[PDB]
Length: 213
Length: 221
Ligand SMILES: CCC(=O)N(c1ccccc1)C1CCN(CCc2ccccc2)CC1
Image (tube, rainbow over all chains, first blue to last red; front, side, top):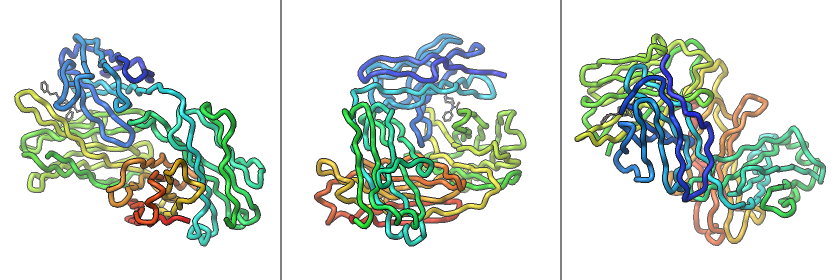
């Protein structure tokens, strides 16, 4: 049993501010701590080694520090590119061990979603099933509510949605929702609509289309 | 330039084994350790071990004895990790990594990871459907279009646009798990509406476990 612990699981900061994550070490490790940055779907990238200085090409925003058992990664002048999960690691003694990870969240101004809707393709309909997609593009904050209405009847139980990670350039989110019906049920109804509520919208936004176009 | 290229995604029966590979290039393979790391989103990062390709020596994390076995082929500058006795709890992304230190300046390099899904279910390749641009997917002269990558198992699919030439404005969403146990995924991109008649938009979907490759052209309607 040897462990490294980061107290903050989530950290929140604005662009241009300084932030720092704490990593505590169970035993004396001295210089031999490393720090990593990871973005979703990507490999980790090392930021700091010797607990105190930075890998080639890492910018000066990142300063590591610590003595023996208490370590901090500090990020000055935080950028939207800095949105990532951050890990400490000890390489002093085996087995090598990482911390639990600290996710950086970027606070920014409210941004309303651009709302788009896609009818099913003819190729999918030939397979006997119909998917309608509702896309909410680049919005903030993350909280958004999507309601599917078919012939103005509120649907439930027949849809699924997913939200992106926070964007590395504009710190927004995007959300995709799919309403999935059989071809037979799809043809029983005329109007397909998704209704979006979001803090940036003074009133709900509805995108809709008539089946048969 | 240094590159670590890892093998494709895997589906493996419980209790069975699979060999992951990590092909190195751009440097003297025999002069630096290859390190291997496991990442499970439900637990975090774990170091598996290192192997030195010059003499084949290894240092394993005690927890992976009998689960992992590291080897290298210096002839092809390739490192390998044999995974065996996998439980359904062992599904993970596995990374290989190496570090070059010169005059105590250090630079790390990582493979892109290999997803290993441990399950008894059979693999299924995706159906790929266009999300056509239309008046209902336009805003301020931009047009949204996409692909719906539906009914596949296991994760992951890799989706690209125009063989990688199109990356700005792409959102490839996290997949959702359907009642059937199959996954579905959306990939969308925003482009100028003015140029819809002259540009071609093709989503390239690849799913290694079923050896499925689809290039789907997305046309307005
Ligand atoms: C779990 C993997 C791991 O622990 N590492 C790693 C990371 C990426 C790829 C390969 C291995 C360590 C990264 C830090 N280096 C520090 C070396 C050093 C110390 C003092 C001065 C100059 C250089 C040691 C290996």
